[PDB]
């Protein structure tokens, strides 16, 4: 009995500004959430507390809005499962398949999606609904765009025995 | 009681050719293994079976050589823990801290190191002893060098409660 849950990670007002293709990614994430709601697919929100609990930056980035009945999980680390109620929430929902949108691609999204894979979930990464910022290290620059693309590349070939991983766009992912 | 184990991933003759800074990475990995041996730190080798079991490509890349008493774990997926004897081997050794060198940075190394973190290990990524190849996706190119650098950047900020993660060079990592 596959039960799909949309997992929306840290799409917060203090996180998304400056990210590659920010407005478009937010628009597509919003569309995904609407399609999920229309299809009766549960939506679980994840918020990063170190953004600043109680401040506007911690709240969802426009134009995203949480609906009644949609759980919100608060976390302090990149892995959304680490010291959180996420697993308990998903189990309560009976989730077997996670459809992931969020930010940032190379930190909370990367760490959470790979943790989900490790835990045994089927996972679908929404290729056009995650983003991050330009960065540099060891004397070389790597753009947010490059990180997003490389992340999608990585996920397209991710394999675990008995599990299914899909890279899909926000308007084509099965809900 | 911290017990450190060096985990050397897929440094195989069919894997490393074409990788960024290949000769240097192999040289430094070899030096790391020698220092580990001199310090009585166990070394565990991981080999990727889909490279071609029984073929020369599956064997360690020169100039690496396995010593007596050093376990070798064989795997079929990016996650070295998935359907393998790795956990059993590490537990037998009583490992609490994994020092990771290997290839490729963005596939088996990425997936295994993050799995190790998830499992509760302390993990040290050896910044100058992992590598991968140039690639491209979604119309943008991202070099092996860029991937290595970004990987080190990522690992430098990885955090889990009660766990320690270190980014360190092959000649400075504590053994």
Image: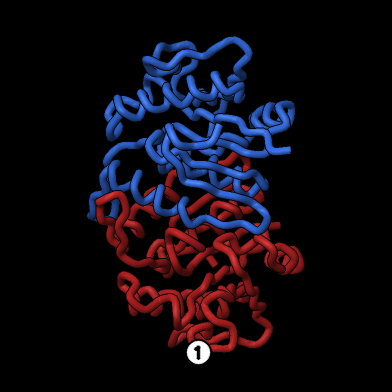
Chain colours: A blue, B red
**What residue sits right under mark 1 in the picture?**
B56
Quarter of the image for the N terminus of chain B: give it: bottom right
Quarter of the image for the C terminus of chain B: give it: bottom right
Count of numbered labels shown in the rendering: 1
Image spot of residue B15 (x, y percent): 44, 76
Of residues B64 and B134, the one drawn nearer to the viewer in this rendering: B134
Give me the chain letter of mark 1.
B
Where, by quadrant of the figure, is residue B66 drawn? bottom right
Image spot of residue B174 (x, y percent): 51, 63
Of residues B101 and A161, the one drawn nearer to the viewer in this rendering: A161
* Mark 1 neighbour class, 10 Å CA radius: few under 14, some 14 to 19, many 20 or more: few
Q: Residue at x 31, y 72 (%)?
A: B21
Q: Residue at x 37, y 15 (%)?
A: A62
Would you say B132 lies left or right of B139 here?
right
Image spot of residue B27 (x, y percent): 39, 79
Of residues A30 and B84, the one drawn nearer to the viewer in this rendering: A30
Would you say A82 lies left or right of A108 here?
right
Image spot of residue A129 (x, y percent): 40, 33
Where, by quadrant of the figure, is residue B135 drawn? bottom left
Would you say A48 lies left or right of A14 here?
right
Residue B50 lies, with reference to residue B58, above or below; the image says: above
Q: Residue at x 23, y 55 (%)?
A: A139
Residue B118 lies, with reference to residue B168, above or below; the image says: above
Asked whether residue A73 appears in the rendered view, the answer is no
């Amino acid at each position: 009995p596959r039960r799909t849950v949309v997992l929306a990670i840290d799409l917060q007002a203090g996180v998304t500004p400056g990210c590659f293709d920010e407005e478009g990614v937010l628009s597509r994430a919003a569309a995904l959430v609407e399609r999920a709601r229309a299809g009766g697919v549960p939506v679980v929100w994840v918020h990063h507390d170190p953004v600043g609990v109680g401040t506007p930056e911690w709240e969802l980035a426009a134009p995203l809005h949480r609906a009644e009945g949609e759980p919100l999980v608060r976390k302090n680390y990149r892995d959304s499962f680490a010291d959180t109620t996420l697993r308990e929430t998903l189990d309560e929902l009976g989730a077997t398949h996670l459809v992931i949108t969020g930010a940032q691609s190379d930190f909370c999204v990367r760490t959470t999606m790979q943790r989900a894979a490790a835990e045994g979930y089927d996972v679908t990464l929404v290729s056009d609904a995650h983003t991050t910022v330009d960065t540099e290290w060891e004397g070389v620059r790597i753009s947010g765009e490059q990180i997003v693309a490389h992340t999608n590349m990585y996920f397209s070939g991710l394999r675990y025995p008995g599990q299914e991983f899909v890279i899909a766009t926000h308007d084509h992912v099965a809900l």
